[PDB]
Image: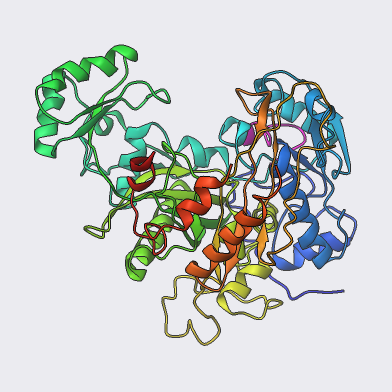
Amino acid sequence: MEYEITNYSERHTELPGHFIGLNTVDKLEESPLRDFVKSHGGHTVISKILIANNGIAAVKEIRSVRKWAYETFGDDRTVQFVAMATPEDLEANAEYIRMADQYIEVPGGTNNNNYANVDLIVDIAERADVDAVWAGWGHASENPLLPEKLSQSKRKVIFIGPPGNAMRSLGDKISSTIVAQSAKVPCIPWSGTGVDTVHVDEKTGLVSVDDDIYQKGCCTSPEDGLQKAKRIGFPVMIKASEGGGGKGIRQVEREEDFIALYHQAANEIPGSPIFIMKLAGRARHLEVQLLADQYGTNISLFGRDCSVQRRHQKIIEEAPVTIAKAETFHEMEKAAVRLGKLVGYVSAGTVEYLYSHDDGKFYFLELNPRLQVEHPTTEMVSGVNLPAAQLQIAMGIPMHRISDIRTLYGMNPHSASEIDFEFKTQDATKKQRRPIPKGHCTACRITSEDPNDGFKPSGGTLHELNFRSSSNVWGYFSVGNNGNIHSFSDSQFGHIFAFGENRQASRKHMVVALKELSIRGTVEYLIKLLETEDFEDNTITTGWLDDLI
């Protein structure tokens, strides 16, 4: 066969040497994938892949990369797959370790003994002979030392995901915010508000904040910060960047208790820089899905609502979003891209936001440089096979040279022209066509119980919820394996996906699916919560759900 051509042999040079992988297409005997890459513009070809993760996550990278490929050069093995198999998983017959094309038995115990491990991941990587690795999410998915050490080998193992440098450019809750203050992302009132000086390392693109700036946004003393609070507007949250999950923070709804609380968190974590933020109330926690290639070409793939949290847990997340005004939502999007370029982010990352409809305004929470288990939604409303996406960007192929990309924007899929993604010139919508979700999708965090007393469960840790009275719904339950705290959870934790023409309807088919699954042997409060208007229009902020029970 033969494809249209794209010659980006220029841009590759300025590309971090850690993006170019050993088996480049300029030194390989001619070959199918060696032709699908080259022509389109990429530099490295990936043939073997290591899955630094298990469960549905690990089965999602497969079905996805085997779909695209079979659709592409037709071969659900074009892109091989080496998986890591942890003891307990072999005793559960994980349907994924089964789907791979081979694998290497890895160390059991606490995940810090395999997946989240980093030297082991690459050692294996060096052993298998892989071109690239993938962690999806969780485990070492966030550690930036993972990719930084993956190409940092005599095997140049590329990394299907964001470059470590993309991560190190994040940082504690201070610099993070200030840096994001740079990409002019409306942030929540704190001590650093108005502090947006950041120095980009021309050579490495590494973004850091220089002390004097990080000290311009801290409380040198308890009286020093107390003064910030008044200037702010109680209640406020006393946090300290190196905040440990749930350590180093106190809410102060009123003066008097400040001095008392300040030292409180400072005591938990010493030598820990403290700052004072403004403590918001019933707002929203939408979430922006943003894509970007290895050529400062960031873009978004819609948004997500998830301000309905279980003590801060994502139970119900529907997408696309209809909450904020369209342009108000549009603003946050370019807002998200306004920062991806900054950190020089790559592949896929979902940026969350605090939304208040009272004012319409919204703030920057944090950047999540790591794919999410809830991308399927943004994938159905856009049709962008993300595990088929990021995988091509890793090989150094532009966004426009991405089958699904053009499709999204209205371009002859086979075409090799560029795209005015920003929609900046009259000569931009003669060829293109602004994106737009197709139907709605509302996930649903389901939880049941099938203990580990003694009997031997059904073979596998991935039961697909094959419903019978719903055409538009997919789900599943996942035997919790190698979590981080749970080498195995008593019960499981699978997601569920529902889709439809509109939001309302999507719900219908959603609940409708929550019905069929309630006749087996959990979701009670679910139908419930969906059958309530406080969700039947998308109004409920951050109180409703918890306000309940």
* Residue 194 higher or lower than 221, as above or below: below
Residue 186: x, y in percent?
Answer: 28, 52
Q: Residue at x 60, y 61 (%)?
A: 512
Does residue 217 appear in the picture of this structure?
A: no
* Residue 298 higher or lower than 215, as above or below: below
Q: Quadrant of the N terminus?
A: bottom right
Q: Residue at x 75, y 68 (%)?
A: 39
Q: Main secondary structure of the magenta part?
A: loop
Residue 37: x, y in percent?
Answer: 76, 62
| Span shown in magenta | 146-158
Q: Quadrant of the C terminus?
A: top left
Foreground pick, 283 / 109: 283
Foreground pick, 248 / 334: 248
Residue 99: x, y in percent?
Answer: 85, 45
To which quarter of the image does residue 237 belong?
top left
To which quarter of the image does residue 478 belong?
top right
Q: Is residue 153 magenta?
A: yes
